[PDB]
Image (cartoon, rainbow, N blue to C red; front, side, top):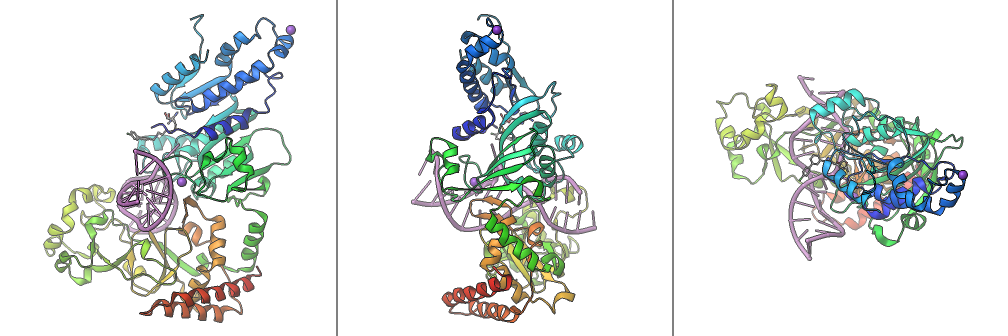
Length: 545
DNA sequence: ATGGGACTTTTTGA
DNA sequence: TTCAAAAAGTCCCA
Ligand SMILES: Nc1ncnc2c1ncn2[C@@H]1O[C@H](CSCCCCNCc2cccc(-c3ccc(Cl)cc3)c2)[C@@H](O)[C@H]1O
Ligand SMILES: [K+]
Ligand SMILES: [K+]
């Protein structure tokens, strides 16, 4: 329900928004945490504000009402005019209310804490500074009634498989004063994900993004499987609009290495570079100049993309794998006619250039005509999960029989020579499938269009796609998920661009040698690495890198 | 107990 | 009718 941001990050975000505030010019700054919780950020905002007022108390006393601006009145002034908080949890608000009160009855000091849905509250005024950590809820874990509200009221950033924190970005931007500064920590995925395209467009066209701190797959929150970034933006009048990008280099480092986050950012554990916000396309390609030069060379040289030459499709989605997937040595497969059985592989079975021998079998239950002819299969294998199967969406609507696969796709797409790759991996692993392998959605497949078979072969494609060049090339724009894991999904894999030049024959021949060695009984993996090194040199020569 | 590594389902909107 | 996206991942062990 409540997640605690590390103190080093909270202090960095508060200092990011307030360290250059001119309290003399504006002694009434409105600082808001829209998901304040117990007050991780607001309590630190109090301390920073208190030092700001006390350090200039005599200048304020001289410039303004001398009786009002006293050290004894700082506590009341902060709570009345400066600190604002909102959270849906009553108990967190009550705890934060006590913590703010205990920072110092005389007369009923009013604290601007609201217990509400920040996405529904009618905010009466805008704010100078906004900080905090919004909630993250995906499309599966969000209520259907609430999602209808979000789709209707937040359609500028929320669509399809978008996340809840997209709307908080929109709300924070909307209620930020002109010239104000916002700084939040959110998941990093919107920086590259397809769902975040509208959100990226909304941020780019409404605020100046001062800084992006990208932690990639490092674990910022303990015992939480999320990858985080810090976004700092303003609504100031500026003409340069360049972004400071801090991208981590070592994902295993501990965040408490230094007393402050800015020490870590300046260190060798991070890299810094600048991106012109006016040059951002629908995609935000945030890489240094060497990588940008590398990426642009490959883009310009290559004339084809995988989408042009290939047909992509996602694997089987049974809707209940335990009901339809069995070990190939399971005795219950004696009850199933071999015409119903398909080879079944997982992502771990995909290597470079080849697929491991399958150990599981899929019951393609869609080919079972009626319940009477194959009652034994239904009663003894599939029916053990009938209650769970009946709860699938297409079963409740009558589109699918209780024993059918939820998304059985087309058999002919799988029962052919094709290339398969895992949906999440640390490296490029594209394999030729010779054995008509089926898979779940953790493996993606594609086959070459007929009109392009004379230009590109499967052996050539796996040669370049598994090379170190294309491993680096794909990861420049790929979606970073967690420690040493990128998404390998068609929405980016099919955008990979490929080339064809005088090195085609030698590259294809080297790949065939690698494939031949990998399929032998006594595999000498040593020569495979040497052949791969030779191929990488050819590809680098081909692409002029 | 916590931190780190291998591995990855099916619900869901369109 | 039927596609493909989505980690506040999930789980195990030292
Ligand atoms: N709409 C909101 N408006 C304002 N504040 C808001 C709004 N949502 C959230 N918060 C605040 O964000 C603040 C910080 S982010 C964290 C909020 C995530 C809430 N979802 C996650 C979630 C959804 C469903 C069930 C559960 C759940 C229940 C019980 C158990 Cl054992 C385990 C899990 C959790 C928090 O203190 C929140 O009170
Ligand atoms: K005065
Ligand atoms: K992480």
